[PDB]
Image (cartoon, coloured by chain):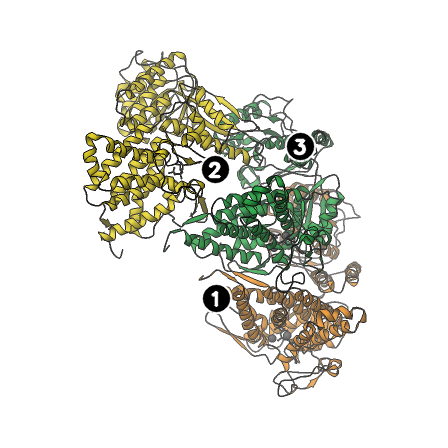
Chain colours: A green, B yellow, C orange
Amino acid sequence: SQTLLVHGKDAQGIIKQVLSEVYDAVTSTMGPNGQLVMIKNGVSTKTTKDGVTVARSIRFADEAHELVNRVITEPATKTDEECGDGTTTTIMLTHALYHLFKDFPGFQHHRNIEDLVERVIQRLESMAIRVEVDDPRLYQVALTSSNQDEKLARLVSELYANNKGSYPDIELKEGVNFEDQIEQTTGRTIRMFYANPWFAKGHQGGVTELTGFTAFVIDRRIDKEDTQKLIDGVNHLVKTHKQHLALPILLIARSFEEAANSTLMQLNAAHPTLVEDGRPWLIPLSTPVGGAIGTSELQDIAVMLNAPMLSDVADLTKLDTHSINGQHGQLELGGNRSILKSTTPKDEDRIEQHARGIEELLEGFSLSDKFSVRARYNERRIRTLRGKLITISVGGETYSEVKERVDRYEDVVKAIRSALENGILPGGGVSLVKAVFGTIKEGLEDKDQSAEFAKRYINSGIANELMRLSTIQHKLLFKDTALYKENGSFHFNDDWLNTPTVMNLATGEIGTPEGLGIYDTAYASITALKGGLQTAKILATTKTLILGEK
Amino acid sequence: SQTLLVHGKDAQGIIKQVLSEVYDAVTSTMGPNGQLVMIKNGVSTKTTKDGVTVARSIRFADEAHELVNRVITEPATKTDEECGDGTTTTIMLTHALYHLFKDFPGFQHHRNIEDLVERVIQRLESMAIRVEVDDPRLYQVALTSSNQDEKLARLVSELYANNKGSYPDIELKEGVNFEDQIEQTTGRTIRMFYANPWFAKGHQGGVTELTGFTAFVIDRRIDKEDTQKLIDGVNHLVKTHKQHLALPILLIARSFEEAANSTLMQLNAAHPTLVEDGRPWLIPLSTPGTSELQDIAVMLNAPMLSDVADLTKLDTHSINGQHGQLELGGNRSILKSTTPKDEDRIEQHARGIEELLEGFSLSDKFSVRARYNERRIRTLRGKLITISVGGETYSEVKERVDRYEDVVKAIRSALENGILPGGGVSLVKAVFGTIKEGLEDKDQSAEFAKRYINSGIANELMRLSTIQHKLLFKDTALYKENGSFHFNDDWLNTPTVMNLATGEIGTPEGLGIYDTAYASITALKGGLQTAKILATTKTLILGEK
Amino acid sequence: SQTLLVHGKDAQGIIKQVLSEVYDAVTSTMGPNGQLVMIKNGVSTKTTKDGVTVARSIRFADEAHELVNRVITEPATKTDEECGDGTTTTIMLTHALYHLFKDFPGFQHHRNIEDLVERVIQRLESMAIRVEVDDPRLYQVALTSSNQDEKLARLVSELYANNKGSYPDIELKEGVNFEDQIEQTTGRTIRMFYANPWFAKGHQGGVTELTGFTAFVIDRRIDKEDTQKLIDGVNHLVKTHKQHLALPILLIARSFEEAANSTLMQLNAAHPTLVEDGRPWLIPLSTPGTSELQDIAVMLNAPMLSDVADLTKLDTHSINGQHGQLELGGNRSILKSTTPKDEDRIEQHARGIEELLEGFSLSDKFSVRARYNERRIRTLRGKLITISVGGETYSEVKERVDRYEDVVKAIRSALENGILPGGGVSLVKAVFGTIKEGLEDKDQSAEFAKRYINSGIANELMRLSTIQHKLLFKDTALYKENGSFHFNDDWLNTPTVMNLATGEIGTPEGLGIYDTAYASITALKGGLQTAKILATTKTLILGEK
Ligand SMILES: Nc1ncnc2c1ncn2[C@@H]1O[C@H](COP(=O)(O)OP(=O)(O)OP(=O)(O)O)[C@@H](O)[C@H]1O
Ligand SMILES: Nc1ncnc2c1ncn2[C@@H]1O[C@H](COP(=O)(O)OP(=O)(O)OP(=O)(O)O)[C@@H](O)[C@H]1O
Ligand SMILES: Nc1ncnc2c1ncn2[C@@H]1O[C@H](COP(=O)(O)OP(=O)(O)O)[C@@H](O)[C@H]1O
Ligand SMILES: [K+]
Ligand SMILES: [K+]
Ligand SMILES: [Mg+2]
Ligand SMILES: [Mg+2]
């Protein structure tokens, strides 16, 4: 509050400082030989090595400093919410790339640094190694992500490897015993969830369990312009077609804005005769689809529940026993996601038939398009359709040791899911070195464009400096070890590039990441570089801080 | 609070400081190097490049400093509320002109600087290109504002060019398909809305749709002093003249205070025989400039009434109930079905407004008077369009929706506010021209030289117009060759800028870089006023009472 | 709040400081010649020698310091909640091992120090001496843990030795007389209690005493979703199978929510013919690890049932009503009369649990898994005893109650887990042994020397085990004046300590100085973990979000 507008040297100075402090703090936790961080919270101390936990909990006293800290940390926090891993690497690159931008100021270099790094990202995306559940490397991924758990990696790799032909959705509950206990189910993690907490059991976003329903899938996003179409629709079914109707009526759609949610709350109050044990007879259910990819996923939700597909909300009126079909199965609605369990063999014929239709669409398209987003999304549909819900109940000697073991399970599930989903890359901070050193040699060697490539990147000094960045992770991991010469030097020659040598920080043996089984998820380490670049550019190109509150 | 009256050197010192800090902050958000600003708000950080956002959110700790900051920033904030764009330019000039006033002190120079800049403003107003929808430059504007979208610019420029004779109001919805889909209507976004949520369908501010009505436009603001005139009025129509009357009865007015709204709720309860499906047969409708109601009157065939008591003395001559189609709303009402009988009455009324603008000065053509009258025309002759944007994902759609909305805003304000060549050029041409005109006119060249040229003002004012062009294209290849000293005659004839998106050099006309005239003119108008103020303040009072 | 992120040298500096201050404070209280600590609390002063009390009550003013203090002390506090003793030793090792980690930095040494100490832990677990109640050493343990109470050790050692064939559960009440008074029972403190006060005698949570019943153990937690399954279940037994049924019907389960409790109140009102002296014929009983219900099932001849709906499908085969004697209670239920027919079923079940532990790893013998299973055994076989401690005053009684409870905890864990020779010796033997084993085994001696001996670790780890023996017997006749004490082979074979009570020198085995193994092992286990943490922390965060 002494000064509320920082500009120029002063502002960048703060950014450089905050970035250095956050970098030093978070990167100290890297690998299994990561050092620890003690964190206050009222009257307790959390000791931890988890980058996402350290990053999220760092705080600065000065408003100006925290202002910047929020920009550095929120992108790290955004990685684990989506990718499930790789915040530390993001911050490390955010730092390293920031200094790269500053070392080559002037906003022609910036255009070039963006272009060069963007090409390095493509070379990672190509390097990505895709794998099947049978593959032995999934263990090695799980092992790396479980902080070297010889026990768990085996279990979860088996679960995936044993169900070859179906991709297991996994849940986690805090168990009771010292030993774990597994429960394999026919359930499906469906992507629908409550529009408003009021529609649940107890009217506060609880987990409503049902043994019968009548769903209807709408496509449109719903807002104040749909409130009348709902009133006409709902009362047309509850008046005319109440005979053949099992409650509740599920209205599954793209989005339910608050103007329409409050309309359907009063439509529930309109017919109090149909309320059983508090359960509202009508529930709006939203999905994070959107776009054309978004239409197909609702079609899956429609097929699983026997509900018809409807383009408009006004189509609710013109319906008949032909188009209305109320199921007597079993469904568990939830705020995060809904889950189906009881599926009559009558239904599973409809589902497997629908899944074959999707499989046939992929059988008749190009090999290049087989690795597209189109194909990958369609396989994401199949595995929703034919998914084997598993519930593991984790256990242990205490309460806290159980809840921590639950977290370590969830880390591994996230890792393995995204491994087969997205790809795996060789670890030990190597893939980035290969990706950069490669991207340089490709443009430097291509005679066609070598002319200008040299002018932009090599001759300017950028290319050289960008090679030195990829070394950072490999240095942070394996400085202060036998793999490095005492003075700190480590040569990244052609011989290294062909067979890159890392050290397993668990055992102590030296070897290749492929040989030693050290692997990273590709979506993490790619998103790390993508996000690192964006948020580095921001920091590097900010010249004004405003702490004015008004 | 240590001292509550600053006078003289001390006061100007504060002003110069605050102005410099605000100038440096806001002008840094212009260009290819154009820098960002990180802004606090409780427990969040807004990163932004938007001048109006930066200006509005700048704060100073010292009372004395913020006192001045309020004067510098409020005129920037006032530009985007009216013009829609151009705050950064206003502040830039406010700064540059302030120093001009201070470099030539003594209040004969000030009279001359005002006079000279006022003449430069006239030379801009003349330079203004009023662009019609047919014009090919609207594409080029849309193209620039769409980040070089070869596809969209075409579509939206066509939409505007294809409806020659009506100005399309455009809405945007997040669609479902990979492809976009357009829905054209003959509708008009009318400025009337519910006085009370009770009068809507379902009695809670919903969207009541109608296929017939009988409107009546009153002028007065309505409160507790009008409750009796309404009771006399409403029952006089519903009793005497019910035969020739389609429900509902719309009572459009300036303002309906809650004392009168509760009276009309009971007047609806008075005649329950006229209630169809819950729809109340009487709706009060308010509007946020007395002739905008005259437009609302003409669109719906309702008569204009000065007093509420005039409701009684009416006849079939003055009562006319429409059987069209109307969608009432809490934000705004929308008309759709318009019989060709009506659209003759509307187009005739629009011509009457157009004729009023044909017989008045060029300086007044950029007034609020003229601009408001054109706002009326486009309400009268408007066509509602709903585009549903689509794409392969969710985020790519919602981002494409934003890129559409940027283009609509640009094209609307382009034809609305008139177009000038961009790249900080038009000001250079306008100043360098104004000098050469007075310097070359032998009649008045005598005194013109004494006032402006010989004093040193003219020279220094040319140097100011260069500011924007410098701030944009310093640190680029366009200033690598010659440098700063090259605004020669050859430049003036074919002014050379750089498209900061692509990287190519060329004319603003060639490269499609254009500014709205009302923005860049208002910038200079406001910049001068608020520069004069700052330059001629010698006392700060932080006495709060 | 001056700074909210400490990193590197600064952070470790704080840790080293806080650890030293806590070490000096707590280790000063060691043994019976332990020095004292005066502790504030509002308007009082607790003088004490109790490590757990000192550790728990230490406070630091600086947030940064207490942040670390919480990490050092919570593991000490966690030992006495589980083990019943040995916090001081934990902290002492936490300190000593921390400095070991720091003396050999680089995280290959750390891997080796962990591996070496982990092997020393195994050598303790093997050294553990297991004891039966008849054994004379239980006295010697009790004597050590009772601060040399010649009177008490005898009593409690007799109580355990006299009930050879049953493990006495012991309670403590603040008595009235100068003399103590013992009350032996055959009973079993069972973990079941009333779900609702209404089901007791007098319908207000009283102590209902019975001489016959028919129990049924359900597993599920019960709520509004089980009310129908109960109505079907209860009436199926009371109608079909009433002949072979002694009232009341006990429904033992995990949890009874209020929705189900009110259902069973009306089911009691349904059959008023079965009400004897107010006693409701049906009582729901809750418990705060699914096999603890299996114990409750086996003690009362009731069957185990997974679902509430399983109540219907039952027969004389599965229904067995006892005619023993049971005292229900709001805190806990108590069994007394057990026909020798039953105690055959119970002892057989207890052997089944004992057999499960007999084929368990030695490391897992000190787990929570094993310790919980022994908690089951002692519920099953035990003879509840209530001692009422007495004395000359109030405070001398309540303090004598605490000294009893210390001894009970010690003796229980002694026979439960094992005993080790005291005087800070067993650790010296365990380390010096572990070295000589690996150093002497030709097979692995090659690499063993490279890792531990040649690096310097092994040497330094031998010097740590000496710490406790030094802290106890420095400043005594057993140590040479200058402070030197030689731990040669001759010492290792017959280790020489001093009884700090009497003053005589001799072996721990000879002088009767013994430690509980689970304490001194858990001390080293926890000491290593929390030393590693402290040694490998480089960042303190005092940020509140
Ligand atoms: N046993 C190992 N030997 C060598 N390198 C390893 C080993 N295990 C993991 N790594 C490497 O360490 C890095 C992983 O860092 P770390 O797990 O500390 O943070 P992160 O995975 O980036 O994100 P988070 O901190 O959220 O886990 C990767 O480069 C990985 O290849
Ligand atoms: N008469 C004695 N002579 C010599 N050493 C003894 C005697 N009695 C106890 N000790 C020793 O003192 C140590 C016990 O320390 P102390 O009881 O002060 O703390 P602790 O057992 O670690 O935990 P707590 O402080 O909670 O009791 C053991 O090494 C034990 O052998
Ligand atoms: N591609 C371009 N090349 C050259 N000049 C541009 C380009 N795009 C925008 N400009 C000019 O730079 C100015 C920057 O706008 P902005 O910083 O938002 O100022 P304001 O907030 O005052 O409108 C615009 O008013 C426009 O005249
Ligand atoms: K980590
Ligand atoms: K003690
Ligand atoms: Mg990792
Ligand atoms: Mg002790």
Q: Please state the horizontal and vertical placement of residue C100, each as a whole percent of the image.
A: 63, 71
Q: Amino acid at mark 2?
A: Gly
**Quarter where residue B364 is shown:** top left
Along the line of sight, the residue nearer the viewer: C86 or A328? C86
Residue sitting at x 25%, y 41%: B457
Let me know if marks 2 and 1 both belong to one chain.
no
Per the model, the C-alpha gap separating discs 3 and 2 is 53 Å
Q: Chain of mark 3?
A: A
Q: Circle 2 is placed at which residue position?
A: B503
Report the disc number at residue A304.
Answer: 3
Q: Secondary structure at mark 3?
A: helix
**Quarter where residue A359 is shown:** top right
Per the model, the C-alpha gap separating discs 3 and 1 is 60 Å
Give neighbour class at mark 2: few <14, some 14-19, many 20+ (Cα, 10 Å).
Answer: few
Q: Circle 1 is placed at which residue position?
A: C62
Q: Please state the horizontal and vertical placement of residue C434, each as a whole percent of the image.
A: 74, 72
Give neighbour class at mark 3: few <14, some 14-19, many 20+ (Cα, 10 Å).
Answer: many
Q: Look at the picture and state if A264 lies above or below C207.
A: above
Q: Is residue B507 left or right of residue C390?
A: left
Q: Is residue A414 left or right of residue A543?
A: right
Q: Please state the horizontal and vertical placement of residue B174, each as a whole percent of the image.
A: 52, 31
Q: Amino acid at mark 1?
A: Asp
Q: Secondary structure at mark 2?
A: loop
Residue sitting at x 76%, y 51%: C320
Along the line of sight, the residue nearer the viewer: C538 or A371? A371
Q: Chain of mark 1?
A: C
Give neighbour class at mark 1: few <14, some 14-19, many 20+ (Cα, 10 Å).
Answer: few
